[PDB]
Image 1: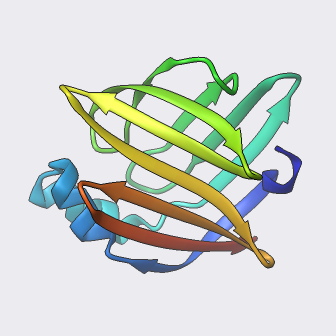
Image 2: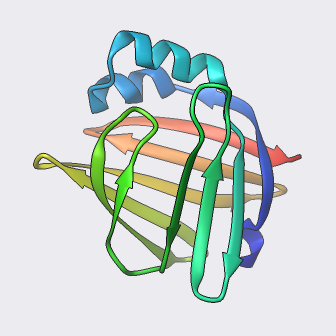
Length: 131
């Protein structure tokens, strides 16, 4: 919860394009998405957590209660069912759509925020620092 609050800027990315290919994102969308380098803004209000990502391409925003399933529209256009829980100090998100699923983990590492995405074995890691 609290350790995640703030504005974060992307510093490094690994295998993100490979992850998007596994998810099924198209060539053009993968291209613009990779050039965008969106930030990440996390805030909490009562029991609702909000994660916002801003970029010149598209801004996305989700507000949720930890443990309650909700509808989410991803940056690449998928309409998925999402659920986010707090486990071992990390935010663990599972997205499900058309019989498929992917996991997105957000955790703290030193003074950084690390996002790890997994799709059928393919793993991508993105590191952020406080802006």
